[PDB]
Image (tube, rainbow, N blue to C red):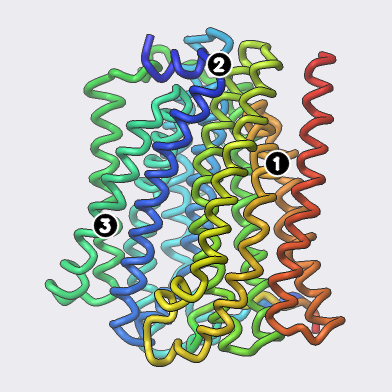
Amino acid sequence: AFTFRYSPSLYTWFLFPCG
Amino acid sequence: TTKGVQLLRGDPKKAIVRLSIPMMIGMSVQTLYNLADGIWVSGLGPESLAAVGLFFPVFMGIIALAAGLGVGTSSAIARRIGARDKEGADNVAVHSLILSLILGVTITITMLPAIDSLFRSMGAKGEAVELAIEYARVLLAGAFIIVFNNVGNGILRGEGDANRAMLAMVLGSGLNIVLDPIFIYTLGFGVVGAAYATLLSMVVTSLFIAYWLFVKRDTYVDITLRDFSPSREILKDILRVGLPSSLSQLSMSIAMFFLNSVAITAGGENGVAVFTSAWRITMLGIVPILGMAAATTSVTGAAYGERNVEKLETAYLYAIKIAFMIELAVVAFIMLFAPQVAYLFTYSESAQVIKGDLISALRTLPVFLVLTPFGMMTSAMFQGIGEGEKSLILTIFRTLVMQVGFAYIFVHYTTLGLRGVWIGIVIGNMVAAIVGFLWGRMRISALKKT
């Protein structure tokens, strides 16, 4: 895997699984 | 004794209507605040917009905890008013205010020393991070004010006083609407000005609530330390609804962050923008359901306090019937005026490219709104009878397992693009609504047996 990333250019957070 | 208590103890259909409407109004003003605020901040440029986006999850976490405690407070009070247990309701209300202090100040002292490294530990850098830290600092300073305001709202809703619950929301959000351009543009404080506008508007709301609770003292419940008796049963009663309620709101946010990733996979950056827009519009039409869900918790609670299952079921099913009819009108309007709505949410030269995709989303996605009342009012009455863990399980099933699961499935196994995301979300919600409705019937037939 789980990652929690922020896009500063989109101003939104993303939650991804291992992959 | 009070008009609100007589509403709660009276005909369930009248209470359901007279408690839900002021709640819908209150939530509509809060929605208006957010939209207006997004417009002000967007004209400050990407750095300010990124600072706000950075802070977004921490803010939602704070809201989840505050609102959670408010719902558990409302449910516990409503139930004891139903049982004609006056000293119990007084004691619940006092326990809730002490809890507001403990939770609110704990959030502040835990997050204040953590925020500088936390926001640096993300990928971003430069000015936007500096603004995000300063922005977060202002709101964390009022974490107690936020919790207190939600607990007060719950005390009011707990005793059938939705009118004053509405008023406090209107005052707070309305004041924030006035202060926003003054602080951001007139005083030239930029994005941190919006944080100050909010903090100040929350403090003023606190003053009205405190005035009603401690000065006017015209609530049904009495709040004194003299008639406060430390109770682990009361604490457990509030937390059995409150804590699962907070987790449900976080399950909602987690689902949105997953769906963001599904949307970028299906349609790229612009597809994220379509999802974000279509979701804001969809969440507009869900406001009446939330208002009707808040009412259901209060009336089913009071009915459960009276040991009156007939009254409980009537309130529950009638909330569904009315929410259903409203959503039909809401969904019909959105699908019919999809191009007109898409115009308003693509109000710029740069957002012009995603308009056509927004229209398609608006002619597909909002359809689930008509099934939502079956699962939501079921979750609402689970909280009314104090069984928050059932409400949590149902919401996790709807938001994470069914919404994200089906959206992921369509994107992985098909080439439908964004259309498959909306269809996955609709199918996911349809299934959960049916499951929720049937679980609700089971729980109610068991209530009649006991």
Residue under pointer 3: B176
Q: Check the residue under mark 1 and report the chain it is in.
A: B
Furthest residue to the left?
B186
Q: Secondary structure at mark 3?
A: helix
Q: What residue is rendered at 80% in x and 31% in y?
A: B441
Q: Please, is residue B144 above or below residue A16 in the view? A: above
| Amino acid type, label 1 | Ser
Q: Which residue lies at the image location 40% right of the left edge and 57% below the top edge? A: B31
Q: Above or below — where is B409 with respect to B265?
A: above
The relative height of residue B307 versus residue B193 in the rendered view (above or below) is above
Q: State how far apart marks 2 and 3 are (Cα).
A: 35 Å
User: Which of B200 and B441 lies nearest the eye of the viewer?
Assistant: B441
Instruction: For residue B117, say whether it is visible.
Output: no
Quadrant of res B39: bottom left
Q: Quadrant of the N terminus of chain B?
A: top left
Q: Residues within 10 Å of mark 2 (few under 14, many from 20)?
A: many
> Residue drawn 34% across and 44% down?
B169
Give the x, y percent position of residue B25.
38, 44
Number of on-image labels: 3
Would you call the spot at circle 1 few (<14 residues within 10 Å), some (14-19), or many (20 or more)?
many
> Is the residue B195 above or below the residue B293 in the image?
below
* Residue closest to the eye, B190 or B164: B164
Task: Check whether the beta carbons of the residues at disc 1 and disc 2 lie within 8 A of each other.
Answer: no
Residue B126 visible (yes or no): yes
Q: Which residue is mark 2?
A: B80
Q: Amino acid at mark 2?
A: Arg
Q: Which of the labelled discs sits on residue B391, or is there none? A: 1
Using the numbered discs, state the Cα–Cα distance from disc 3 to disc 1 in whole angstroms: 32 Å
- Tag 3 subunit: B
Under circle 2, the secondary element is helix
Q: Identify which residue is drawn at 84% across, 30% down.
A: B442
